Image (cartoon, rainbow, N blue to C red; front, side, top):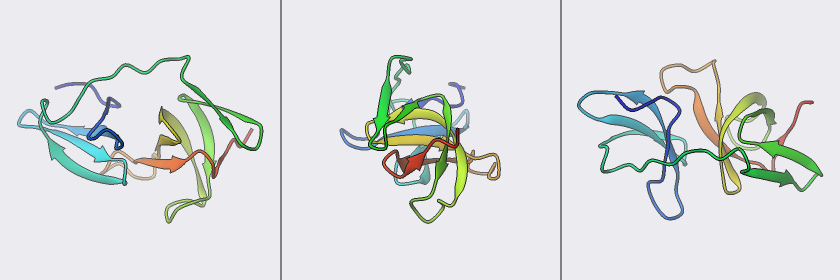
Length: 115
């Protein structure tokens, strides 16, 4: 069952989130922006820390829980909601897509706060 929105580290430099949970296995999204079924052991558990904060080179404050615009990348060109933040990559959520949970990561370097 696990929980939705849980982030998992697939590798020492790759991160993914859970978009579709299943009893036979859990569907996690690869930081590359892909969805692949995985097992509890094939994934890890990490609690988000409110202190986890990042500063945008444009003098902008970014938080794991905030709204930012995405202009870099093929899906960029729209605004998303910052749900999970990891290193220079943050997991954004998009209600437009529900089949894959509308979860995708972007480079905070190109992410700009709308407000």
